[PDB]
Amino acid sequence: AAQTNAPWGLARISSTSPGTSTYYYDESAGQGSCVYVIDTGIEASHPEFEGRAQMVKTYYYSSRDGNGHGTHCAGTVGSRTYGVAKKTQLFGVKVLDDNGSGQYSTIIAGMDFVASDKNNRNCPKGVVASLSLGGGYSSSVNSAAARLQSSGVMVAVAAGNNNADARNYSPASEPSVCTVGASDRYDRRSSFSNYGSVLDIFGPGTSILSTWIGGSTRSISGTSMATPHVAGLAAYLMTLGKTTAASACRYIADTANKGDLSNIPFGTVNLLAYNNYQA
């Protein structure tokens, strides 16, 4: 299939070159996969989710996304217009309050929740978790992300927006998950994007159009926005039987557009998420 006038990030992950506007993707579209969005929640009532989004857990007084961040990332994973995997199931896990902040303990609990909650769900093509969050290095947060991955979930996490090595940040520094840096529409590393050897892949992260609360849309920049691209791509590639949860990150790295990005510091992978779709 094709989506004309797609957000540049969707077009980018289906092309070998920047600057296009069409998103090319197999029509399966992540159908049968599930993506937990671990964030400020999801406004499941947004028409862009077409009833494929639902809240499954909150760690605050309300399940509703009073911030937008989570609804925005869920949109990039699998919304109709702004989503990589347009038929995937979205599950909201609200670990950040409406100010977007959340204790390390809360974020760890949310990751443990997903590891077991997935056994209650029907995701015959596999499970993905998208974690557009992070803070300073925490062994315990890292361990939680690793547990989620080993439990059978493809974990994608943001490298962080500090323009520094992601090794000093969690869960970005967990080696076993898929740490995602951000690029802009001109195939530059995003100005804010963390880097380092722990990074596994880059995704579109600068000025990313997606859903927003109040049934709205806006553009936001952040490695938090590159992460759902890769999570969506993983769900997409899993539905296609190209890869599994345990191998998706390395599969995406293997099939990525190589050496296209600029300002990638020595020691950081020069890899941009690419769905390799052929009509």
Image (cartoon, rainbow, N blue to C red):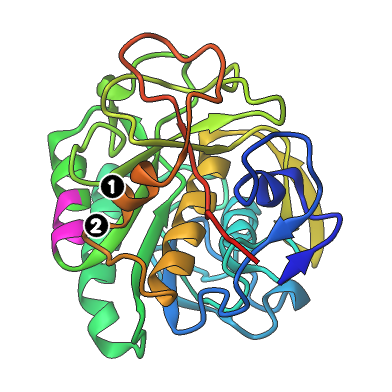
Above or below residue 89? Residue 225 is: above
Image location of residue 214, percent across then percent down: 79, 64
Q: Look at mark 2 in the image and give the residue it sits on.
A: 247
Q: Residue at x 51, y 23 (%)?
A: 193
Above or below residue 203? Residue 53 is: below
Name the amino acid type tagged 1: Arg
Other residues around mark 1 within 10 Å, as few (<14) / some (14–19) / many (≥20): some
Q: Residue furthest right?
A: 5
Q: Look at mark 1 in the image and give the residue it sits on.
A: 250
Image location of residue 203, percent across then percent down: 53, 39
Instruction: Pick the quarter of the image with the C terminus.
Output: bottom right
Is 149 inside the magenta-drawn segment?
Answer: yes
Is 170 inside the magenta-drawn segment?
Answer: no
Corner quadrant of residue 244: bottom left
Q: Is residue 212 visible?
A: no
Instruction: State which region is magenta.
Output: 146-150
Marks 2 and 1: CB-CB under 8 Å? yes
Q: Which residue is drawn at 43% across and 65% down?
A: 237
Name the amino acid type tagged 2: Ser
- Looking at the rendered structure, the secondary structure element under dot 1 is helix
Q: Residue at x 27, y 20 (%)?
A: 168
Q: Is residue 84 visible?
A: yes
Q: Residue furthest front?
A: 279
Image location of residue 61, percent across then percent down: 47, 67
